[PDB]
Image (cartoon, rainbow, N blue to C red; front, side, top):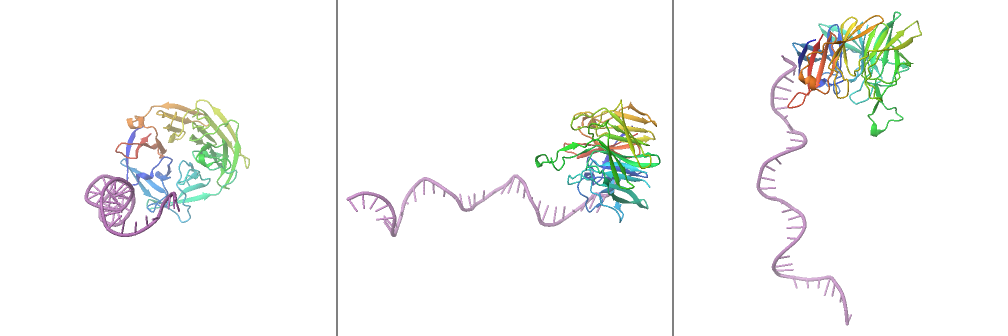
Length: 341
DNA sequence: TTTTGTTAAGGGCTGTATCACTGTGTAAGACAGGC
């Protein structure tokens, strides 16, 4: 794992905590810019290309049949296999939470210049309340595909919300949501094993299962060291969901996850306590019914990283993470690194 | 029969309206990078 500093072009201000990166056919893209999109890039979607440790953000265009989704911070994202990206929830530049779900796909790649399709999917049934900091992944069971959504935070319900605490947030009830994108429907499942709310956790999806790692629970103000396996079977039109607690769970919120090889993932970064950062790294190796979490060699962090109180980042896709920390003195607002695996 | 106003010309304290003067905030422009 080699750490490398990155320089940024004129529009560095766009990058903020809560941003996301999506990878299409090796090409990386950036979404969730700070502020509302400007004339320079009306979509809020950017080619995110790092050449010789220099990062350029170049505006990307939408197809004629696209939505223009608002920039979203801490939305739930996953990748769907004809490869597309699912974005659900998040905070908008006006601090509202969206209940909408957007789908990003490549509409046209002409002479290495990508046009995107952003389509909004209506959701009916048990729609999950607007959220941020929650997970969504795709499971495959019995030749059928289903979305699994869990966790996050939201504002108080319209009945109890008051202007003195107008921005107060609470964890959502820990109901797993099965989401059929084909029909646009959502079903909620209460499980006894998920008693507490959880947000900013990590989710790993393999076949018919999603594992839930770390995260932070507001009510207890704990980052629990639990690992949850959630299995989904889809026999015809009657889905079934079952959860199992598995000991050996890491305790981490806001960690970043990257795939280094099939059935092996690396977990880097995050927070172990409010004032402490998780400097260690984990390797997760997947079996068809087993999951293994092993400590790995901690990278050669610089002193700036070691002493930073906050860091934020995203997975670039090619086993490489894009990281960031703030700096004061004279000078830059943010300093960015790329950690390879 | 007892209190006040009043005239005119004119003489000091007092109150406020400027002086001159510059730093400084805001904004009207100019300008140059998007390797």
